[PDB]
Image (spheres, rainbow, N blue to C red):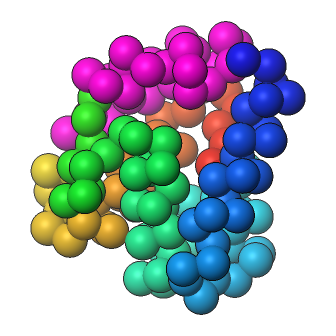
Amino acid sequence: MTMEQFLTSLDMIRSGCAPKFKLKTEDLDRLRVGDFNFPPSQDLMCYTKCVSLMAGTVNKKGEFNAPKALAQLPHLVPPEMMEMSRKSVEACRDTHKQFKESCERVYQTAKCFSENADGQFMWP
């Protein structure tokens, strides 16, 4: 995967999920560069679940699938994002266990990925 294919994918994914929710463009812009340090709306949290289902790394209850993600990494991120992605998955695999609502679970997991990124991190 090229960093180029990765970016196009990020944009395609956001276009499919955005429509379902009422979101602020500046919020999406912040998530895109891995800045999860701001209070998310419920809709924004549900946006992250939508994005994750689309990517296929969570189930409908918002539970993160670490093994699937770890297996699928090569088809998820460019090669230079692999290692960092793998470690973040390793550090955030149980985060969702502390939350009950599906949207929040995913959002919290994604936040965790962002805080554990040893380098550039991006979100659709």
Q: Give the residue drawn at x 54%, y 80%.
A: 20
Horizontal side, residue 69 vs residue 62: left or right? right
Res 39 visible: no
* Rendered view: 103 above or below 23: above
Q: Residue lying farthest bottom? A: 22
Whole-percent x and y of residue 122?
A: 67, 43
Pick whichever, 30 or 59, lies toward us: 59
Residue range corresponding to the magenta coloring? 67-94
Whole-percent x and y of residue 115?
A: 50, 43
Q: Is 89 covered by the magenta stretch?
A: yes
Q: Give the residue drawn at x 14%, y 50%.
A: 97
Specify the principal SS of the magenta part.
helix
Q: Which of the image's four quarters has the N terminus?
A: top right
Res 47 visible: yes
Rendered image quadrant of residue 78? top right
Whole-percent x and y of residue 113?
A: 46, 40
Pick whichever, 115 or 47, lies toward us: 47
* Rendered view: 12 above or below 66: below
Q: Give the residue drawn at x 85%, y 29%.
A: 4
